Every structure is written in C-alpha cells, then in structure tokens.
Amino acid sequence: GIYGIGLDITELKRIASMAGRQKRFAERILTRSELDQYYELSEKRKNEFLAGRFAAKEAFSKAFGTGIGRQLSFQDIEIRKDQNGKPYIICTKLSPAAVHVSITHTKEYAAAQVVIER
Amino acid sequence: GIYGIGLDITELKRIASMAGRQKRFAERILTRSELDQYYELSEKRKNEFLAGRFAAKEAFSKAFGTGIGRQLSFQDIEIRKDQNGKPYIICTKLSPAAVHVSITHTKEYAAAQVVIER
Amino acid sequence: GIYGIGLDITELKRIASMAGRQKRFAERILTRSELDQYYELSEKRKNEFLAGRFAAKEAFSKAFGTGIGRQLSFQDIEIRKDQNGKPYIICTKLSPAAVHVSITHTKEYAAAQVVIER
Ligand SMILES: CC(C)(COP(=O)(O)OP(=O)(O)OC[C@H]1O[C@@H](n2cnc3c(N)ncnc32)[C@H](O)[C@@H]1OP(=O)(O)O)[C@@H](O)C(=O)NCCC(=O)NCCS
Ligand SMILES: CC(C)(COP(=O)(O)OP(=O)(O)OC[C@H]1O[C@@H](n2cnc3c(N)ncnc32)[C@H](O)[C@@H]1OP(=O)(O)O)[C@@H](O)C(=O)NCCC(=O)NCCS
Ligand SMILES: CC(C)(COP(=O)(O)OP(=O)(O)OC[C@H]1O[C@@H](n2cnc3c(N)ncnc32)[C@H](O)[C@@H]1OP(=O)(O)O)[C@@H](O)C(=O)NCCC(=O)NCCS
Ligand SMILES: [Ca+2]
Ligand SMILES: [Ca+2]
Ligand SMILES: [Ca+2]
Ligand SMILES: [Ca+2]
Ligand SMILES: [Cl-]
Ligand SMILES: [Cl-]
Ligand SMILES: [Cl-]
Image 1 (spheres, rainbow over the protein chains, first blue to last red):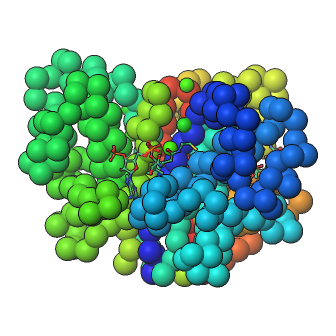
Image 2 (image 1 turned 180 degrees about the vertical axis):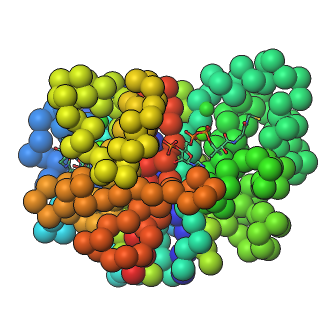
C-alpha cells in the first residue's frame, strides 16, 4: 500500500534570496551527488535546479510524516535519476527502496510531489 | 490498490472575497473540529487555513469521483492531524480509514492533493 | 503497487501563444475524441481545456518514465471521462487499464497529476 504522500510548491524568488544571503545555502540543501550536478549549471539554472530539489525534499518530508527538522534533514534525502532522466528519491534512513517523485517548473515556481509505498 | 486521486490549487484572494461577502462562509466549508482550530487564528492565517482545507476537500471530491455537490458536501469531509502535525482525511460516508492528503502554501495559492486507497 | 507518478503545471499564456502561432497546434496535442470535445468550446475555454490536457499528458509522460519524445507522443495518450465527469487516462501502448489523473485550474495555470499502477 501507500505509507504517505507529499506535495510542495516552492517560490523561485525566495530560493534565490536565500542563496544570495547565505554563501553556502546550496550546500545546506543538496547532497554531494546533487551538488555535482548543480555546479555545472548557469546562475539561472542553478536556482531552478535547487528550488526543485528543495520542493522535492519538502514533499518527501511530508510523505515521511515529520517535516524537515529534528527527525529529518535535507541531507538525509537524495534525488537520483535513471538513464532516461526520470527522478526518484533515496532516503537511507527509511529503506533502500526507490521513492516516487515528480518535478515541474513554471515562471515563478518549482513544484514536486512524492509517494512512499509500504 | 488505488481507488482515486485528486489535485487542487485554490486562489487565496477568491477565498478571502467569499469570506468577506458571506458572514458564515467558514462555517459552510469547515466541520466543527476544523473550526475549533480556525477560530484561534489571525485574519491572515484564517484565510490560509480555510483555503488549504477548501483545496483539500475539492481534491478529495475528485478522488471520490463526484466533485462537490448532490453526492458530497464539504461537511462530509474532515481534515485531521496526527501528533506530528501530518494531515489526513476522514470521510465517514466512504469508510473509517484514513485517506492520504498533503497541503502546500504559496504567496497566492493554497494547494492540496489526495489519494484514496481501495 | 505503483509503476510511476507524474506532476505538471502548465502556463495558460504559453499554450495560447503556441495556438496563435500554429494553426494546427490543438491537432498536435489532442486525439480525435478529445478534439470532438474541444471544438464545442469558446476561445477562452478551448485554451483552458487544451492547457489541462497538455498538463495531463506531460504528467503522464513523467509517470511513464520517458517524457514526450521518441518513445511517447501526445497522440499516444487519451483523457476520457466517466458519467460523473471524472477524468482518467488510456495509453494503449502501456495497457488497456485506466490510469489515474486529476486536473485543476487557476487564473494563470492548468495543472495535473497522474499515477500509473503496476
Ligand atoms: C512541512 C515543512 C517541510 C514545510 O513547511 P512550510 O514551508 O512552512 O509550508 P508549506 O506551505 O510548504 O506546507 C504547509 C503544510 O505542511 C503540512 N504539514 C505540517 N507538518 C507536517 C508533517 N509532520 N507531515 C506532513 N505534512 C505536514 C500541513 O498541512 C501544513 O499546511 P497547514 O498548516 O495549512 O495544515 C516544514 O517542516 C519546514 O518548513 N521545515 C523546516 C525547513 C526550514 O526551516 N528550512 C529553511 C531553509 S534551509
Ligand atoms: C470538481 C469540483 C470540486 C472543482 O471544480 P472547479 O472549482 O470548478 O474547478 P477545478 O479547476 O478545481 O477542477 C476542474 C476539473 O475537475 C475535474 N472534474 C470534474 N468533475 C469531476 C468528478 N466528478 N471527479 C473528478 N474530477 C472531476 C475535471 O477534469 C475538471 O477540469 P476540465 O474541465 O479541464 O477537465 C466541482 O464539483 C465544484 O466546484 N464543486 C462545487 C463547489 C462550489 O460551487 N463551491 C462554492 C464555494 S462554497
Ligand atoms: C518531461 C517533459 C514532458 C516536460 O518537460 P518540460 O516542459 O521541459 O519541464 P517541466 O518543468 O514540466 O518538467 C521538468 C522535469 O521533468 C522531470 N523529467 C525529465 N525527464 C524525465 C523522464 N524521462 N521521466 C520523468 N520525469 C522526467 C525532471 O525532474 C525535470 O525537472 P529537473 O530538470 O529540475 O529535474 C519533456 O519530455 C518535454 O517537454 N517533452 C517535449 C514536448 C515538447 O517539446 N512539446 C512542445 C509543444 S507541442
Ligand atoms: Ca514548502
Ligand atoms: Ca478548485
Ligand atoms: Ca502568479
Ligand atoms: Ca510542463
Ligand atoms: Cl518557498
Ligand atoms: Cl479558487
Ligand atoms: Cl507551460
């Protein structure tokens, strides 16, 4: 069955502001594997990539049932992708299984949803 | 398996307008348990809370397969939350089981999604 | 279980622009059955209908795992609806089973989500 679901719509301007005020904001949100992908992008694409991963992790934290905080850090969640470019999540604290995720972008937002199966 | 899924993105300004034109709009959308939580909020938070519950119930009505109308009222759906703050839905007309739901907020919208299992 | 999930938020203005620049844009995105429904709408409703179907098909392509391209065309996906107005998807290339979908509209967007079961 389904353990939990999560949805999030993140504001591009907020992510850009936090990145502009905190020199290491991206390192706070992304894992090393995620950063390897992030570092190759333009200033604009970096913001969209980061906002989408931020939305995916907040959505995951809702499906997990705790939100981001004492029980779950942004660093405990990793978005990976298969050979076709389809994203999926790995949260070792949960299990080794792939968790369902989908991301979408607009002019002002980066949105994502997650479904964790039993 | 999955009985149905539902998604909704509600406009904060529309909800605020309806609440401003109808003195009992919140009572139309929310159950007594939901209102107990609503009454404790500021004018601004009330609007966001109400818009999110409205989105969650419209999303539920889509997963249910009928929409809001003759077969389903906003009063037949209740959003509850566990000790961690995770929301879930109860629709007695359907079954006593918890229905999956997730909510997210932006500057102009309150959005939600629902998944009803078999 | 779940084979895949997909989410998409499409910009109404972009869809209107493509339809204004390409005389056969609707025919590119919609199947014959979908067009039969589209042709009956006003200019404004046509745009909203088309944007919602576009979002639903992009969401489906993400759940399918390939995106829209060489392995999947907009024409391979069809949104149908039951007697209550609830939409569902049929992708013959996948299987004859109904695929879960939900659509929602705002002032500037048409959004959709999809869940494909095993
Ligand atoms: C849940 C979380 C991930 C997102 O909260 P947010 O950004 O404030 O708000 P969102 O609008 O995206 O989500 C709001 C909703 O989460 C849902 N929620 C709250 N706790 C939850 C939990 N434990 N499980 C699932 N959903 C939960 C609620 O329904 C709530 O909306 P509501 O108050 O109208 O019912 C929160 O734990 C959080 O922000 N974590 C801290 C991270 C942080 O401070 N980051 C700074 C940048 S590095
Ligand atoms: C489905 C419902 C919940 C939401 O409709 P809405 O606000 O007009 O529109 P939304 O943009 O959020 O959703 C539109 C979509 O619902 C989906 N829909 C319609 N009937 C449906 C049903 N029975 N089951 C599942 N989905 C359905 C459709 O795909 C439709 O978009 P489309 O016409 O492009 O295919 C509708 O039944 C409703 O508005 N109920 C009446 C409530 C009301 O009048 N409230 C006033 C405030 S108190
Ligand atoms: C995936 C697709 C459907 C949508 O992509 P898009 O419009 O460019 O962008 P969206 O913002 O909606 O989706 C972006 C996300 O798709 C997800 N994605 C990419 N490939 C994917 C795949 N194979 N399976 C599932 N998800 C995938 C990604 O996470 C990506 O965001 P990210 O780069 O931050 O990780 C793409 O295949 C596409 O646009 N198809 C071509 C259709 C076209 O050119 N149409 C013109 C109009 S007729
Ligand atoms: Ca958020
Ligand atoms: Ca709605
Ligand atoms: Ca906007
Ligand atoms: Ca898209
Ligand atoms: Cl945000
Ligand atoms: Cl609305
Ligand atoms: Cl778009």
